[PDB]
Length: 99
Length: 99
Length: 98
Length: 99
Image 1 (tube, rainbow over the protein chains, first blue to last red):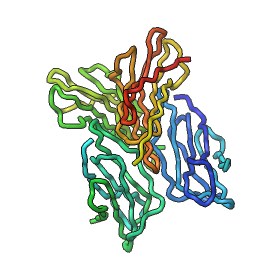
Image 2 (cartoon, helix red, strand yellow):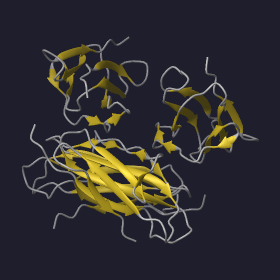
Image 3 (cartoon, each protein chain N blue to C red):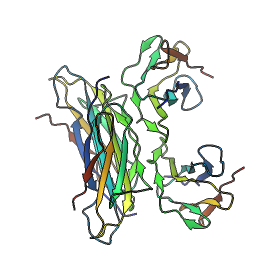
Image 4 (cartoon, chains in turn green, cyan, blue, yellow):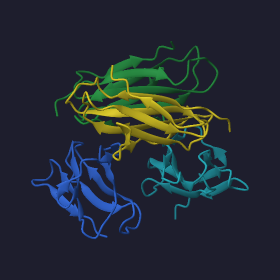
């Protein structure tokens, strides 16, 4: 039941190109315990109606969770993911690199 | 691999209350083949950000799928679910009954 | 984070009939914390090959989990589900009824 | 509806080591239609204890499915995955390369 720090990965479903519709993902992996605060950001503002998968687990109880939303990438808009867990001293913000 | 018509069920996660946040679900079950068009409606208009589960299956390939969205019910707003499948002669609209 | 005792439900996927293949389910619901020990039993003995769904959660962190296995029911064999959690002093055994 | 041949990947969850518990995975991806026969083998014999994920899909209906089982690797035992689909003339056997 020994605690593990989460691994945060912010990416888009398909290679980024403006004007069209796509998906913004925030993959949180290999953490313990279960209770985790995950939020998706658009220009510093929290995104409304974010979808999330069910909490997947391994034999030694390491958790895997995915937070995703439908979005239109533009030249103006900046996207990020905010994660808060018991292992972290402060909430972590991981920015999305349109690359 | 034999034609099965889908069973549509429209319901809310918790007992509905005006002004209180809830979830609107559209459960589609026991259908074949896999390809199905499911849409959640608000006053006749298609809801933008709709979340969906993964397609679960049985031994004889009968499919089960859930379409859900976060919503705040009001007295004015009417909700429904539109389903289109290869078995159906025309798309079926199932209204949400909160009574 | 305030504790919640689990609700255990033991059932078969389809109506049971001897000699024919089925699935034995153990649905554990509305519990906190996450760490739960769920085991499916055959004549008091632990079943080695058991599948499980993914841990679903609510706003206040109440958990929902399903443990299932493929089985061929007989009139000799008895089935049950053993659950151990931090909220309980001794593990709870819930028997399956045909 | 267009036809797509499945991509089969056979791998272990953690790097394989004799006597230590592991998981054998058979990842089937980018196929159409849905109906697919997947089986995990041990020395040519079909494994009875097999768990499987839910069928995930894209906009153009391309399917993704994972078949997994708990196993203890030895130097003597050989593992493989057998897949049979409508696109294939005969079932395909993909062996698990340990190294």
